[PDB]
Image (tube, rainbow over all chains, first blue to last red; front, side, top):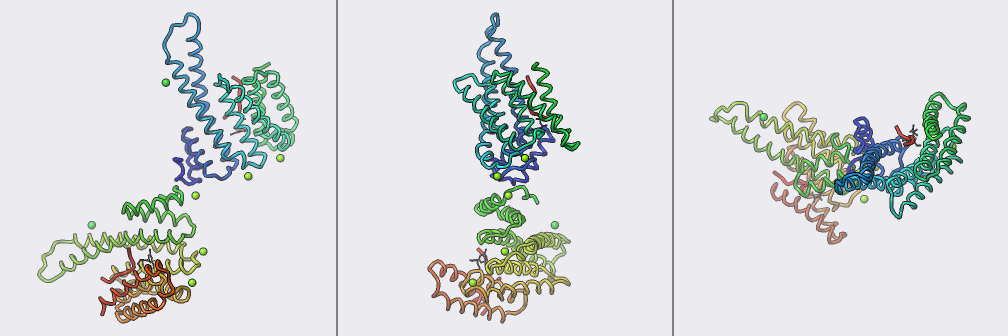
Length: 236
Length: 236
Length: 7
Length: 7
Ligand SMILES: CN(CCS)C(=O)c1cc(Br)cc(C=O)c1
Ligand SMILES: CN(CCS)C(=O)c1cc(Br)cc(C=O)c1
Ligand SMILES: [Cl-]
Ligand SMILES: [Cl-]
Ligand SMILES: [Mg+2]
Ligand SMILES: [Mg+2]
Ligand SMILES: [Mg+2]
Ligand SMILES: [Mg+2]
Ligand SMILES: [Mg+2]
């Protein structure tokens, strides 16, 4: 690893600087190096890991969607033949995106998940595992598509089971997990009714528990509840 | 510290590479960075520290002696005035040499010596403290000269007291300490008889203990005994 | 595109 | 110059 010679604390420090400079590829490489030191991650460090890779893969997904739309238009009736370039370049972006997803999944498997015993860390990592399988599923078209979708589903389901037992309904990790699993149901699993039911039940159970929270926790929880509400408005 | 971001193990690895490449300034900087990590040093790491700085200061001392000899000749009767350049350049080299000695002494004081409890480490560091005060004494000409000489003497004497109680007379650290303390007596303290007596007693006590050693230990000890013999031949 | 957990 | 502990 190219980060093997850098101190863990220096990698963390540089990940924070990279975030401030909006250098998310660097941020992700620093956080990968920090994970590979072999120690468990703190709450703040887990957030840095997730932010870094979400920004990297988010740019790749946006580019893939632009190219996929151009390619789909090229395959309409009446569209001129322009050669293999659109497919080739969409495939290039797709392969890079898959590589980033495989990198994140590899960090989770070696060995973040197995070492995560507290609910807050274990749910966080299992949510990430579901997310990166979901991003693989967004671009999958072959014979492994069903297994990729089931891998996302299985990780989300394990995270949900733990989150319901071990964390209050307003916990931001629990809420973000439920948000992303609902998106999985709607966008990946062809299950819009399950997506709607999960978003509604999650929102309502969080609403009923807001009275227990401080002002700052209330702000954290209601921010994610608004995302659930936004999706419910889009979907209904 | 410019090495603060590098892993301790990487600094050690690079010190060994620098030794192989005869890059002793780099070697010393890597080992300084390793000491500043705050952990105690192993036997091998102590040897790397000493080799690195001995080579750096050895080059400075050789250069200082060349320049000091030129300067002394400039102050002979009949020598032409050539301006301040020889003194200025001798002073430049001298200041750099003093800086390296102060750096080593600072590492020993913060905090190698205080953390060294085993005889092999404590004697090694106290010998080094005597050596670097001795190198300061070689160039000292002012009102602190006597105190610099006494600082070297005091460190050597503490190392000798521990070495005689805790280590066999053939131990290479004990032998190298006695060798260097004898050189201190001869070259710094104007005590050639003490130098001769120490070298002879050290040699004879080691000779009587060689029968206890393996072939490899015998080779290690007799190598240093030959240095004591070489000095005795020079001095008598 | 539905909103997922970001920013 | 006397030999000290080096090399
Ligand atoms: C506001 N917000 C992001 C929108 S859900 C979060 O609290 C958050 C951040 C990160 Br990193 C991970 C998770 C996981 O659930 C949740
Ligand atoms: C052969 N040899 C060098 C000539 S004394 C040594 O065993 C040696 C090496 C180092 Br580093 C430190 C010491 C300290 O006593 C001794
Ligand atoms: Cl291409
Ligand atoms: Cl100069
Ligand atoms: Mg470290
Ligand atoms: Mg653990
Ligand atoms: Mg709990
Ligand atoms: Mg100790
Ligand atoms: Mg002993």
